[PDB]
Image (cartoon, rainbow, N blue to C red; front, top):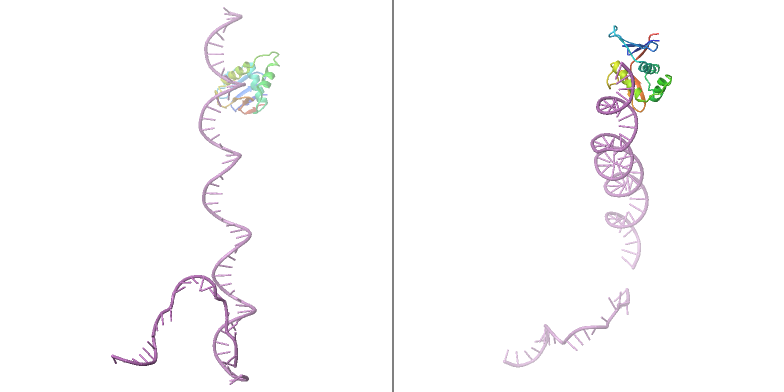
Length: 110
DNA sequence: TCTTAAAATCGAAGTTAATATAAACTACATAACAGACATAAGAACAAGTTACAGACGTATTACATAAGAAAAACATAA
């Protein structure tokens, strides 16, 4: 099932591709970790998910354990490549002591 | 001017506490006493208002600590 974010971006959890409607010619390439994080965020529309729970769901299924700086770096790359605002709540933000939040709308293509 | 009648005086204090006999009836107007009512003064209960106090609740100020991000240094592979 393909998902649409904020009526602008399109992404699929199965092939890890990003398409911007403003520039449909340029496909945006994302890493597996950040793509899985964004898909986990999209699976729970617009409510807080824990850093601990999201981290353990993303990386223990991978079979290997990493430190918590990895999640922060992955989110930094996600915000940078999506060209989301540096600290304003436009698409993805961080809620301290509670976890991570998404603002972009969810539109399932199929 | 020589009798002769009036007039006046006669110690202080202290004490010193009443008497005491002797026409009737009628008519009228006025004052006084008693009862009741209304009025001015008074008291009690409740309400409005205007303010100040008392402790609680708000905003100004100075931070402790922990999560997140940037950066410098290090180890490793080409």
